[PDB]
Image 1: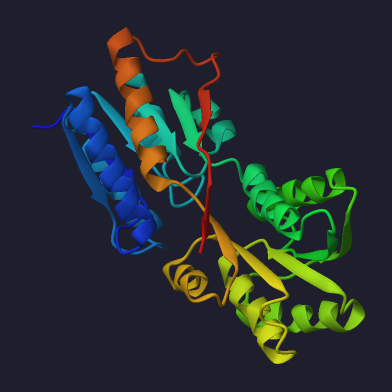
Image 2: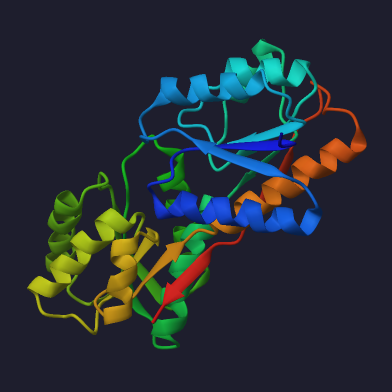
Length: 288
């Protein structure tokens, strides 16, 4: 049976349920069969590396895959590439450095541009504030992590190009609704003239909308989030959170199957020296 296979992170998370449907749907259009696999828990690094390994011994033309960690699947993917399997990295980037040393490569990496995500949620505040503008802040995530710092850049640059906006306080905050509430109230005392605050995660965001529920500024103050969890989504339907910048799972999976099928057609796997393709998929701004 099937000519293509897709390993994902898990399927108890709606994010990955939406990705599966996008690869299936996109398959029915291209004329290719697909088998979608995943290991139960988000922290099953070994159980996914066993999964992938089992698939490698079957006869799949190509295999797209979302790695739990950046190095848990380097040896199976590099093996897969020597056999001539058309691999396509999804969501998070696999350690290319390690992969090089493994003697392998990938046809393409398909992810969401985290900087654009930050500018998308900052730009939403900009337009809502209007000409008048006003003061804003960015509750950052934890330092060292690229994915939250990327949202930190984009959101910063987008408010600097708006010469009617005042960035009061972009300060660190580890991914925590409690610690997000505590630095929230800190900015609301230092600068109580704030009209909105974008947060670099949906966890922090509900902790900042708690600091606005405190001072009972709910309505004037605009909270924004990222990732778009099912929880916060509801919030935004109820007027409790202003908005959140979700990803596009379905398009990431569908684009990933498209690039895999395109490499197969070519009849030759990407050279080692050749860098992979790099498609970014647009983020979505979920609003009332």
